[PDB]
Amino acid sequence: PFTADKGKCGLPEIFDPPEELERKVWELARLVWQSSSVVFHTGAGISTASGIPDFRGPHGVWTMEERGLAPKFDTTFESARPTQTHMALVQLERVGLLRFLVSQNVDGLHVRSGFPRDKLAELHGNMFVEECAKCKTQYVRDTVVGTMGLKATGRLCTVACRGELRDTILDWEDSLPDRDLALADEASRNADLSITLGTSLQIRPSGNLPLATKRRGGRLVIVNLQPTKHDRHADLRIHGYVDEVMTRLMKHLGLEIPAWDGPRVLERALPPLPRPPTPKLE
Ligand SMILES: Nc1ncnc2c1ncn2[C@@H]1O[C@H](COP(=O)(O)OP(=O)(O)OC[C@H]2O[C@H](O)[C@H](O)[C@@H]2O)[C@@H](O)[C@H]1O
Ligand SMILES: COc1nc(N)nc2nc[nH]c12
Ligand SMILES: [Cl-]
Ligand SMILES: [Cl-]
Ligand SMILES: [Zn+2]
């Protein structure tokens, strides 16, 4: 825990120049158009523009710790707004261009953005979610569950049980939730395109799942300001702010980024909404 490997921290940022960035976001659009099964992989980089620091960025939690400084929050977890990137991912699932969403983030923003939980794997847990030890019934709360490391929160199960409710926040020693990891692995294996957004891919097995897409000829796109463990295996690397990338991508796809109405929980995905017809590519 104290000694836990926190990985490569504070690597230099890379910025694709505008012309190279415009061309690569068009190539990503082309790949999304050509792909039957698109899986997105998200980490802490997608929440930095909402005031939540990442782990391994220049001002990341672990980076700052290494230099004896503190991470800085410009929001509480409760007052944090889903980013343009969060809301882009809601719309991409709604129009049938996103098959599955695998996230290492505990910030609860995917769930609160209105993203359907049956298409989301929260590999590291969710600050807002507590789970009954006895019946496994999960509860999505409007405030952070006040503990971490899978401890008793103090509340009891209300299913018509009184079981001990525990937080879902994995400590260093904890196995990933079997249900989320199995569905994430199946989604990544079956994918013909895996897009990583604001993750350095340094944590096993989370960071390895996008590689699973590469088996059987699938494509891998990595979007990130810093290098990532698997840059080598990427068909496409985009070095820019994930919000700039996703807003340009949505524009190329003819999709609007929907308004956020405040925190809303959607359990199950609907049939896809209408989407624009596809360009002639080849
Ligand atoms: N706006 C942005 N646009 C693009 N990239 C960004 C942006 N902001 C940050 N980044 C990049 O986003 C990347 C985020 O990388 P890391 O900080 O390792 O976070 P993880 O989600 O992969 O951490 C994995 C687990 O490790 C922890 O212990 C927890 O358990 C985590 O769940 C960096 O390379 C930034 O350059
Ligand atoms: C574990 O929750 C957290 N998520 C993120 N992203 N940053 C944190 N800094 C302290 N705790 C944090
Ligand atoms: Cl500081
Ligand atoms: Cl908070
Ligand atoms: Zn229960």
Image (tube, rainbow, N blue to C red):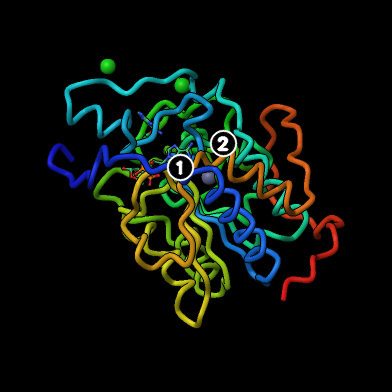
- Which quarter of the figure has residue 277? bottom right
Identify the residue at horizontal 66%, vertical 30% (top origin): 263
x, y percentage for residue 90?
A: 69, 46
What's under tag 1, amino acid-wise? Answer: Asn
- Of the 4 image quadrants, the one containing the N terminus is top left
x, y percentage for residue 222?
A: 46, 56
Q: Residues within 10 Å of mark 1 (few under 14, many from 20)?
A: many
Identify the mark at residue 109; answer none if there is no mark.
2
Q: Residue furthest front?
A: 19
Query: Can you say whether 189 is above or below 175 in the image?
Result: below
What's under tag 2, amino acid-wise? Answer: Leu
Q: Nearer the viewer, residue 50 or 111?
A: 50
Q: Residues within 10 Å of mark 2 (few under 14, many from 20)?
A: many
Q: Nearer the viewer, residue 53 or 13?
A: 13
Identify the residue at horizontal 42%, vertical 20% (top origin): 73
x, y percentage for residue 252?
A: 73, 52
Locate residue 162 relative to residue 146 in the image: left or right.
right
- Rounded to the nearest angstrom, the CA distance separating label 1 from label 2 is 8 Å
- Of the 4 image quadrants, the one containing the C terminus is bottom right
Identify the residue at horizontal 52%, vertical 33% (top origin): 128
Q: Residue furthest bottom?
A: 216
Q: Nearer the viewer, residue 73 or 31?
A: 31
Query: Can you say whether 170 is above or below 210 in the image?
Result: above
Identify the mark at residue 105; answer none if there is no mark.
1
Query: Can you say whether 50 is above or below 246 in the image?
Result: above
- Which quarter of the figure has residue 54? top left
Is residue 164 in sight in this rendering? no
Question: Is there CB contact under 8 Å for labels 1 and 2?
Answer: yes
x, y percentage for residue 206?
A: 39, 57
Is residue 124 in sight in this rendering? yes
Mark 1 C-beta to ligand 1 under 8 Å: yes
Q: Nearer the viewer, residue 236 or 100?
A: 236
